[PDB]
Structure formats: C-alpha cells, structure tokens
Image (spheres, helix red, strand yellow):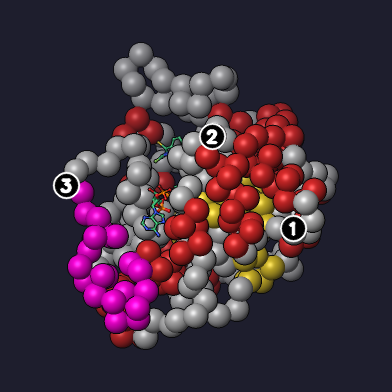
Amino acid sequence: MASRILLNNGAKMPILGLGTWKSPPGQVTEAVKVAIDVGYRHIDCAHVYQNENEVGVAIQEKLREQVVKREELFIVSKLWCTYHEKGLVKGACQKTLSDLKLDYLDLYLIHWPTGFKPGKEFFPLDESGNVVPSDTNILDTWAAMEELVDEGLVKAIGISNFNHLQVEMILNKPGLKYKPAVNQIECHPYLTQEKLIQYCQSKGIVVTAYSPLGSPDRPWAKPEDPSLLEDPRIKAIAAKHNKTTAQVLIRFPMQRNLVVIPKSVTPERIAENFKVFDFELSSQDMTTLLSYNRNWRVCALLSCTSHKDYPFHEEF
Ligand SMILES: NC(=O)C1=CN([C@@H]2O[C@H](COP(=O)(O)OP(=O)(O)OC[C@H]3O[C@@H](n4cnc5c(N)ncnc54)[C@H](OP(=O)(O)O)[C@@H]3O)[C@@H](O)[C@H]2O)C=CC1
Ligand SMILES: O=C(O)COc1cc(F)ccc1C(=S)NCc1ccc(Br)cc1F
C-alpha cells in the first residue's frame, strides 16, 4: 500500500506511526530509535504522557546520526486540557517543542474537547472527585491553535476525541481560518466508529485510529474485559494470511483509509508491527472484522463525564 496520506494542509502523513502512551521513560528512547531504524517515520506524542523529553532524545540522535532527515519525520503532539485558555496555548506548544528537541511540529492536536482549570495538576478535582472545568470554549481554543500555524510552530492542526457535533462546531466556526487536518479517535474491531469516520471523511478530515490493539496495557484493564489480540476469530483471519493477530489489527484501519498508531516498547514487536505493507485483507475479511463491533471503549473517564464538552454521551 501507499505509505502516506495527503492532508488538507497539502502535507503527506505516514499512515503507520509509533504510539508512546505508557512507554516508560527508561525504555521509550530505545523504542523510538529502533522504530526509526526499522522504518517508522511518524511518532505520536503528548505532553500528558510525561515522556516527551526521552522521545526527543531519540529523535535528536537519529537526526544527528543522519539516519533520517527532519523533513522525512512526521511528529505529532497534543495540547493538554489544562492549557485550553488563549494565553496558555503558545507556551504549551513551546514546552513540547523544547522537550522533543524540535523547532516545529508536523501536527498539533487538541487532545480532548474538554478544557480543565489551569494549574500543575493534569486532572484538577473538586472535593467530590469531579474534574474542574474551564469556561473556555472550544472555538476559542481553535483560534489559538490557528495562531500556532501562523507563527510557524506547527505545520498542521487537528483534534482528538471530538464527536460528530463537536467536529461540526469546528467546521462551522465563524471566521474559521484552518480546518482540522485530522481527528484522532479510538478505533478497532470492537469500537468500529463507522458513523463518526464517515462524517469526518466526508469533510476532508483524515482519521487516525488509536488503541488499534485494544490497549491491553491500559491501567484500568479488568482481567475479564474483551481482548482483541486473543480473539480466536481474529486469530483465524491472521492464520489464513500467515500474519500475526497484531498485523491484522494494524492492517484493518489502513484499508479503511485511516492512519494507525500502535504502541510498543518491545523491539521485536516494533519490527513486527511495521511489516504490514505486504498483504491485503479481502473485502469479506474487512466486513467480518467490522461485524465484531460492540461499542466498547478503552478511553473514557468517569471523573470527566459531567463536563459540558465530554464527548461520549453522543451517539457518535
Ligand atoms: N488521542 C488520545 O486520546 C489517545 C491517543 N492514543 C495514542 O495511541 C497509541 C496506541 O494506543 P494504546 O492505547 O497505547 O494501545 P495499543 O492498542 O497500541 O496497544 C499497546 C499494547 O499492545 C502491545 N503490543 C504491541 N504490539 C504487539 C504485538 N505485535 N503483539 C502483542 N502485543 C503487542 C504493547 O506491548 P509492549 O509495548 O509491551 O510491546 C502494549 O501493551 C498510544 O500509545 C497513543 O500514542 C491512545 C489513547 C488515547
Ligand atoms: O488520553 C489519552 O491519550 C490516553 O489516556 C490518558 C493518558 C494519560 F497520560 C493520562 C490520562 C489518560 C486518560 S485517563 N485519558 C482518558 C480521558 C482523558 C480526558 C478526558 Br476529557 C476523557 C478521557 F476519557
């Protein structure tokens, strides 16, 4: 398959990237170095993951080493919820740039559509456990993102975890200067998101699928939850193609014209997960994988569900 997808800013984005959530700081430098050595050219990062400095060490080494040119890398980061106010967005982006050892990002996302009270705590809580919102509206945060483009800090801007009505809000913003280039959302056979994906694709937005393996290392996993990697129906599709279950799970979103960002810190798996450009799933296989949808989510958070902009009360 074609290795990059054209964005609405005219740039090309690699359809396979390396995820970094939960990658320990002591292991993520080696993971990113190995990824770049074996061909990855897209890295998905975020301030809230607490490992951007170590990701940046890897990127800098490979650039210094002349393993890859900066123009060939596609580095993504994300604005955390406690930085949605106008006067905090530039400094948040600049901190991420400083940590990653870069003078621009390829893509900067609003991480969640919910703004939180600014401060040191990533999840500021009231005395009863609810997250404390900010009275920032999303549209104002988008205008601050647009300024980053115009200042040269970021080449493209986008959104993450926005539902159908929030995407439409952004698209209908008075005075909109830059459309979102990407919406990064959870997507896998148990949460297939057909409705949201068709909406975004109809509007020219590229969708990135996160948690494509079902995030088996999520901190809130419960021993009895569904497990994609162990699903014998997916194992059977994999066996028919002489591929691993992970390889099928990564190829699946690629054939839906999605970008996909599997995470690993294991060098062998980082390699395995990149070898997905030499087989095709049939239409029948694709439809079968889609049939496994159960509307199950990795990423949701009870403490945030009363926030006015919490995204997952809506159908899509
Ligand atoms: N925008 C947002 O709100 C969010 C963005 N994301 C992004 O998406 C990325 C991917 O999602 P994530 O939730 O991390 O989970 P994934 O679905 O990518 O699963 C990662 C887990 O799968 C394991 N694994 C990886 N490759 C294989 C393999 N070949 N065989 C068996 N097990 C494998 C990893 O183990 P090990 O590492 O030990 O090898 C790790 O435990 C994140 O890291 C982050 O960058 C995720 C959630 C939310
Ligand atoms: O968020 C990620 O990338 C991966 O997950 C996280 C990654 C982190 F480093 C810290 C917390 C999360 C959580 S708990 N994320 C869920 C979540 C956060 C905020 C809101 Br609004 C709703 C929600 F569902």
| Vertical placement of residue 130 versus 289, above or below | above
What separation in Å lies between label 1 and label 2 (alpha carbons)? 22 Å
Q: Earlier in the sequence, mark 1 or mark 2?
A: 2
Residue 247 disc label: none
Is residue 241 covered in magenta?
Answer: yes
Residue depicted at 64% across the width and 59% down the height: 37
The mark found on residue 224 in the picture is: 3
| Left or right, 231 with reference to 122 | left
Give the alpha-carbon distance from disc 2 to disc 3, as whole Å: 30 Å
Pinpoint residue 97: horizontal percent, then vertical percent: 73, 39
- Location of residue 239 in the rendering, given as x and y in whole percent from the top left corner: 29, 77
The quadrant where residue 36 appears: bottom right
Question: On the image, numbered disc 2 is attached to which residue?
Answer: 26
Determine whether the beta carbon of the residue marked 3 sits less than 8 angstroms from the nearest atom of ligand 1. no
Q: From which residue to which does the magenta span run? A: 224-245
User: Is the magenta region chiefly helix, strand or loop?
Assistant: helix
Going by the numbered disc 1, the residue's amino acid type is Val
Q: Which residue is mark 1?
A: 67
Give the alpha-carbon distance from disc 3 to disc 1, as whole Å.
43 Å
